[PDB]
Image (cartoon, rainbow, N blue to C red):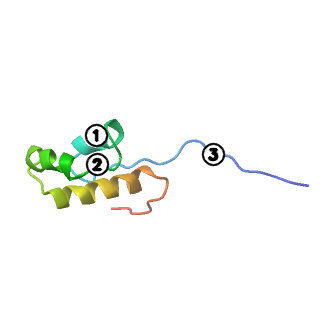
């Protein structure tokens, strides 16, 4: 015989990584992997640091992807 598998509805992230959501947009608005040039602005916008922000971006993808068992 034989068999298969199917899906569809999946879980969703409740808690937000950070209030820097403003990035979530640019990530898929201008580029998923921006450069300092961009960080220069956000740095002030979200009173964050070019470095601190970067981390947020890298994490973004993780959350997006289907991989992420991290449960608060």
Q: Using a 10 Å C-alpha cutoff, classify the residue at mark 2 as few (fewer than 14 neighbours), some (14 to 19) or many (20 or more).
A: some
- Please rate how many residues cluster around mark 3, counting C-alpha atoms within 10 Å: few if below 14, some from 14 to 19, many from 20: few
| In this rendering, position of residue 62 left or right of residue 9 | left
Q: Nearer the viewer, residue 71 or 53?
A: 53
User: Measuring 13% from the left and 57% from the top, which residue is drawn there?
Assistant: 49
Q: Is the C-beta separation of discs 3 and 1 under 8 Å?
A: no
Quarter of the image where the N terminus is located: bottom right
Q: Which residue carries the number 2 mark?
A: 34
Q: Give the labeled residue for mark 3.
A: 7
The numbered mark, 2 or 1, whose residue comes first in the sequence reads: 1
Q: Is residue 19 visible from the viewing direction of this image?
A: no
Up the image or down, 69 lies above or below 29; here it is below
Q: Residue furthest top?
A: 29
Mark sitting on residue 59: none
The residue shown at (30%, 51%) is 15
Residue 26 in the image: x percent, y percent? 28, 40
User: In x, y percent, where is residue 17?
Assistant: 27, 54
Q: Residues within 10 Å of mark 1 (few under 14, many from 20)?
A: some
Q: Nearer the viewer, residue 33 or 23?
A: 33
> In the rendered image, which residue does mark 1 sit on?
26
Residue at 26% of width from left, 60% of height from top?
55
Q: Earlier in the sequence, mark 3 or mark 2?
A: 3
Residue 28 in the image, given as x and y percentages of width and height = 36, 40
Which structural element holds mark 3?
loop
């Amino acid at each position: 015989g034989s068999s298969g598998s199917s899906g569809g509805i999946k879980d969703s992230p409740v808690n937000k990584v950070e209030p820097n959501d403003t990035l979530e947009k640019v990530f898929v608005s201008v580029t998923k992997y921006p450069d300092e040039k961009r960080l220069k602005g956000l740095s002030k916008q979200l009173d964050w640091s070019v470095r601190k922000i970067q981390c947020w971006f890298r994490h973004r993808r993780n959350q997006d992807k289907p991989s992420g068992p991290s449960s608060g």
